[PDB]
Length: 131
Image 1 (cartoon, rainbow, N blue to C red):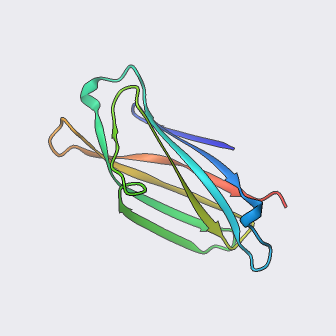
Image 2: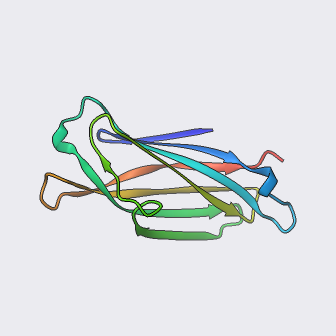
């Protein structure tokens, strides 16, 4: 399914997928991939060009266990987003429950504005196994 959040001229889109071949009911291991799309509208000023510094994830399963993940980059990269550009990457996550959800944000800095740093919301997206 598809989840979206926009901040300023930037939109973050998340598509999720359940992978049953890697998922078991015992031990409870529910494997999901997610594909993230970070895009800046064509109509934005080229001044707003910005570079991804870091990520913050809050991951919650269906029994109230929570995990925080924070670190530099996404999958080892620090992409630059400028008007019309799209950065896409894929990652995965496991839950010990049939559902879980994730939310957080990316921290960006402007390339052409001295020390202007800002956070871009990642939409909350739920992952749920039908069965």
